[PDB]
Image (cartoon, rainbow, N blue to C red; front, side):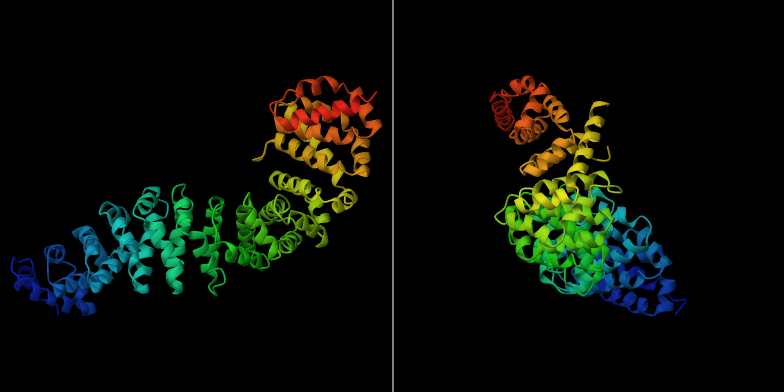
Length: 507
């Protein structure tokens, strides 16, 4: 056991075909005896000998045995410091090009233990070019092996933009996405989804993950019994979903997200809402699918249940706003919000304690709801108009005498746009006018921002259809600013402006 030792050193470090080969099969043996090995990491001349013969050999049993030893040695915090102080990291990495499975398994786990416990190991693996080597190993098929390799990658990539970009350039995204859609082994899907989460916050990795089919592959695991796997999939999907507008094959993912809205899990709900929010922006087919699988219903229930938790209601409200315009079933969806009892909660979200991003999204949603005639009356009855007017008046003041992510100019435009639509209904025009808004709408004709001039002249165009209001609009001196706006580069602006003028000068 203890005394007769650096014998096998000298024959290992030898320059002969048989000599070092059969000598290595020896340290191998003795490293297995737990308390016998805990003494063999002592010899710097011994430790480093192991390393060399591994780096340059031919023997599949030399290799196996050298690696397995380092493997075996990598369990004590003294056992690791030895491998490290010796410099096996670069050789171990070099062993990641080997074609012999057992050699792979031994290298990876040694690096793994080193990456896990040993000071300074992350930096030395990077220097050795391990990232590239680990990425190329992702095409293997042994799940235990792949689990370890993906975990090395997560350890290296976390908080290290340089490493994330090397992973990108080595084709990481595709190979990690392949893993997600091929395997079922939880431990492996989990660590892989962690690697994808870490990369999904990277400006360059994100579209590559999306181009590789990331969104669909991640979707596959959203009903796994493993909660840590589903959640990590939800976080990654969320980070990526603003880049996935152009993706097809999205129908399964979209249906699962709708079901996930009903979850008891707050992070689950929060994620699904935000993912549905992003994937529905502009892509009218996603709109179509989400509505076809009951999205409106589910989004209304989610908003009713969230109460004042803005992490939920804001993305849910943005999703409902996407879903209530500019697709073939926009109109059924505008109706469905009312039918599932959404109109009161949506008006309620305009009031404190709601913060600005929510108010903004909510106003946008009201705008859309108002395109549907049968919403005109309940919106009024729920009190939509006076709050939208107060929000407008206050936000316009803030813009003159000059917030939390949002510019008051957006609330001005949003509120005026919402009132423009609501003004289609005659009783609504009475409330709007009775709130003495005409002076304000006229001032908004002078705004620098064209979209504001558009909704302002549009709402005046709606109001000017009643005799009494046209007179009022004229008394505000609207003729002059409308005169100049006839020449706006914006056709909406120039057209609305001419309809007001027409309706005023029937005298």
